[PDB]
Length: 304
Ligand SMILES: CCc1nc(C(N)=O)c2nc1NC1CCN(CCOCCOc3cc(ccc3N3CCOCC3)N2)CC1
Image (cartoon, rainbow, N blue to C red):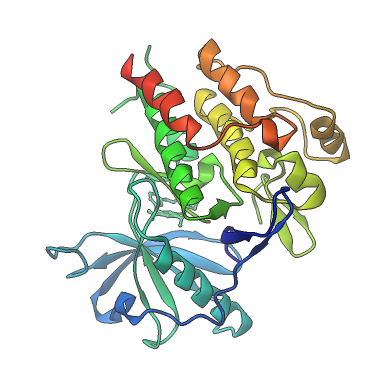
């Protein structure tokens, strides 16, 4: 399953919607790539289902150079049910189009053998590991406060683009934001990690989840605003576990349903703490849009 899904709303209230299955749609062949031009690298991450590696793709760009890449693929010893599920993520990503703040799809290998899907390369890694790594040399090669603000604006216009395309990202967090050349960052998708609770066949990032997700399984564009506020806390904390010190247990569910909100993090202005509280409104109608967070932050940066 892909934590990024496209929705078609069938009503007014929040739960009136349904997801889109591409299993019956046809795959566009112009994304097809030959495996001849994939020169590998070192594993860059592998859970249970699959992995994503570094690779080198000669003649895959407009001009044509090496241009390192990341390649998502299975390793379930050639499975069946898990394979077509990946084909449908390919079909969706192909129709999302490029945005400057999304880890974009560059190609795929379909009938070429075992299924490969080729994504952009972000050399500086996920934002979580990038933030925590620079806690030493934070200053008031090493980052300003406009970095914290530019990061927030880029993820916002990225989620603003996912809303235009009628998508929802059900796992917005710092581990899923990746830094590439020149302090530009891009949203991406994807059991020894403390952040996900497993509950049935679902793996849930409880501390990032909006109450309507924790308690009734609703995922809307406004549920991503809630997670975005949590990420806002992740950025201006320099990346410490949201709700620090509190374990994910039954007591944490009573926390969120009773109206718990995190305190202002150290590196945050009084201004953008207010914006964090907006996303943490219990009523999702009371929450700010992703458009509204174009101007409200893209301006806060210009003063820096
Ligand atoms: C699809 C998701 C993805 N995308 C991409 C990409 N398109 O670039 C990508 N890694 C991932 N998986 C994520 C990455 C983070 N890890 C944490 C532990 O694993 C270290 C990975 O190390 C990296 C992987 C990358 C870049 C840089 C690094 N650093 C290694 C050391 O130097 C600094 C950064 N590349 C979890 C899974």
